[PDB]
Amino acid sequence: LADLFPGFGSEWINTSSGRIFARVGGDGPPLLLLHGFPQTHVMWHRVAPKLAERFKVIVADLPGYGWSDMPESDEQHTPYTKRAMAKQLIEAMEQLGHVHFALAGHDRGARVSYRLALDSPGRLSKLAVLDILPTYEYWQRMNRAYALKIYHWSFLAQPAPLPENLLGGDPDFYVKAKLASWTRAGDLSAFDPRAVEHYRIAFADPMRRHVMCEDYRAGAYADFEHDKIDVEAGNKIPVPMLALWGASGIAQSAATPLDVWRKWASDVQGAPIESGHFLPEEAPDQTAEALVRFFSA
Amino acid sequence: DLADLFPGFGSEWINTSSGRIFARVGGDGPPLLLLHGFPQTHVMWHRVAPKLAERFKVIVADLPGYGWSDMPESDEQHTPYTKRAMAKQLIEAMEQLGHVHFALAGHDRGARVSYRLALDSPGRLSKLAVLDILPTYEYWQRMNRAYALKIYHWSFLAQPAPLPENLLGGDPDFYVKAKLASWTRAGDLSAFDPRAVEHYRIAFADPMRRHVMCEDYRAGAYADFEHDKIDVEAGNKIPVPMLALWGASGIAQSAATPLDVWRKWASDVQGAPIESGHFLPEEAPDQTAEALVRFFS
Image (cartoon, rainbow over all chains, first blue to last red; front, side, top):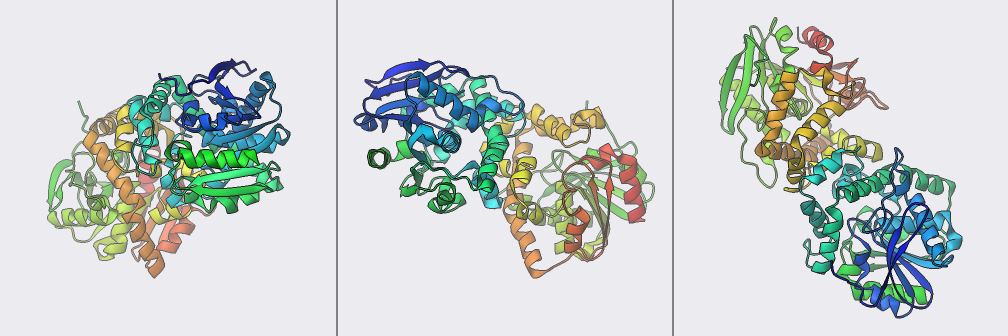
């Protein structure tokens, strides 16, 4: 596998829930970058160098993803709930001396991020979420059109071992199918092939695949329940937040993203990026410029 | 090695303009067409058909594309697998036997053919029974988190080829057994005759058959929904006396009973819950057989 972060160090951060792998580079204020599915920390490889010019950039594999350890799940998928992932990444950041840091997350990592901001807002200076709406919102907007577009939300949430067994016959196909279908082009051209190989290799591990399903099971159940409580209780993220989404990404299908996020956060700025779902890879300059601008204010 | 579960039934290959329909035919009396659904074949009727064949000419048909029926070439609209087209093909099939007016009981996908047949061509039907379905439109219209997780396959199998086909290729024996198992009251395969399971398993073992099933569900998400919506919007009701049976467990029984929903679609509908999961004729054969006999007589 390629080193896609020349000059970045590599850290295995112990937490109570397992080691978090991260690439670490730059200097300045700490900025944690979290990837989503079916990716690893390397998805940040085109924007992290630009962020590293101004921030101490920590590009972490989510708990259970990439080279991070896989906490054994349970019937409630607890370690793969965004609440648990956020606590675990808070612990990891603490291990590095970062008790207050900026956070940008993409996809699942963005869900960890806004859950972290709801549970532990004191930990965050600024939060950026890329191409997501809160999990609750996706579920509450899950009509026929949306059920078809993000079928995987319900497919991967099926009880084990059903998605695992189906994924295992040809894992390469599925990871590549998901990378391609959520891009603007609908193919792999936006991805550095070396990055694709990272994603495919992670996806090749049955245990990694199971973790992704656990993440999605959490997504369907506990994560939804957690969000539901906050939305019903009128709890908004108090952390200044940037919501970026791809003009042809997943978030914008369910709804107008800024309107949704203004319901969830008291200080939200939003901007679309002409991109599919994979903003930092489909639109690295634009994404990085948006993140740099936002985190630098 | 495929057991004959209809001793005394003949086996008919019925030619239609879209290909052959395979049917077991037994009994004597008014014609009654029994249509299975997914992921089964006509043999699902093996426990109730002999009781019906005491009073009716029972035609136990493989749906177009299913079982031993020929598989019409699909198209970008999945036309041959729309319930409208399947109805039309089964009407042609019944006409080959000289049955222009017949009773119809359908389960699952077959019940969707059946009520569509009833909407498009109600003069072909003396009486209609639908087992453990609501109209396709109602499924999609009530689409929410709970139903998306429960009937996830409605959106999964409707994904563009070859995504479901490839995934189903991952473990087809597991998938079909998981679907049969998970939709019963028991949660396992114990309600099924093992020899029937072998039929379902072998049909499901054929990639082309699996592709047809996906074509069926793609129709179910697109054209079938559009056809139902037209009837809802035009207020078109089924004028055929109809019996709606559903499993107290399984795919419908929620807030309003299936009967309440069906009453919006049918002018003359009676309904009863059967102590069953989804697979009424196999989980609850005597009760199913009794209700059908009583209704069709």
